[PDB]
Image (cartoon, rainbow, N blue to C red; front, side):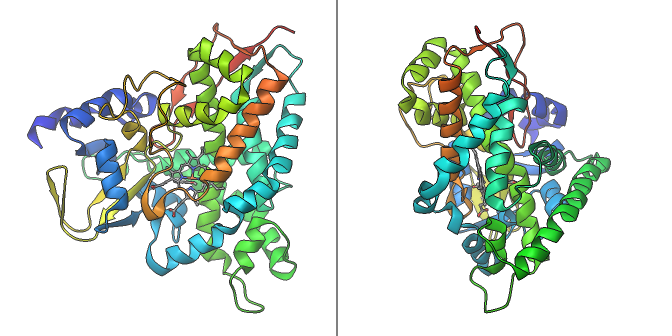
Length: 402
Ligand code: HEM
Ligand SMILES: COc1ccccc1O
């Protein structure tokens, strides 16, 4: 596309460090555009992301680096009967009435445990000491991974993140950095060594862990789903499900710190925490551009005639700064009117874990603000955000008077 020749000079490093300047141009120039270093069409606006995500002429496809990492059948990358089965497999523990039965007793004692380690220190780096551990410890216990330390769960999602988002391609469309999948393969090998004995056990002795239910639910007597059939969805969980509530919490906190009067409002009135989190997810979407769809028929989207079989990456984090919807979207504003957003995606492949995720983030922030009501950001340290596929702050140094 001639007038987008500037896109040939966009680099993977640029998109990882800060994709918003390129995507502001895309939303104005070409809401559906082929980005050479990603080797794919990308959807950048709210209208195009929502249309592709809900279109009957599209179905799910995994991004190239996502498929190299997760294989088949990753719940995000399949359709039809396999997708319906995998959705029926994951949905029981995520049902709102079910989450409401036990989410408080799950997350609140975990939040308190991690807080007790630093709440009298006067300083902390909340990404590593709080947001990530609460997120992974909550989900890890729900899954049946109680014995996998939070440090290890955090390491695995970081390696899987880098492998799944190792998207750069060269002039021939080949991956530019094939070595960057090695740590994804190493994480998977480690996960197998830990999880294979647990699956061996659960097949014979089912329990209330979610993965035990994935093996047994809905199956004929004495049968379980084959572990190779469920492992790619285990990996989907050990990346995003483990990573994103912590990133959403942390981005919400960075946003609140950027508006001190609003941080104060929320600490004084914790019933505003859900609204603060919803704006946090719009402001820096944790899953920023990690999923995609593929056309099943020739289709015209945003004036582009796509043949059948065309992948489109859904850059929901850009869509959530669409100035057709939002005033000054790069500013965090608690008091934005509560409008639809796309941080959980849309359509038949929209996030299955919204209700659980929102509660994890809510409870963690409630406990944080109760424990440390005079929490302040350490303005001697900068907050750097990183990531194009998954995005969040790489640290969050704070201070408080002791
Ligand atoms: C703040 C935290 C989270 C955010 C922002 C988030 C966001 C997303 C997004 C954008 C997608 C892709 C939707 C699309 O392609 O249209 C997705 C997929 C998915 N998410 Fe969430 N997620 C979060 C936490 C979780 C958690 C904790 C779980 C599990 C307990 C979960 C389970 C899933 C599943 C199973 C899918 C795949 C749905 C499918 O392809 O059918 N997510 N999520
Ligand atoms: C819930 O986890 C994910 C969602 C979308 C893409 C990758 C994931 O691991």
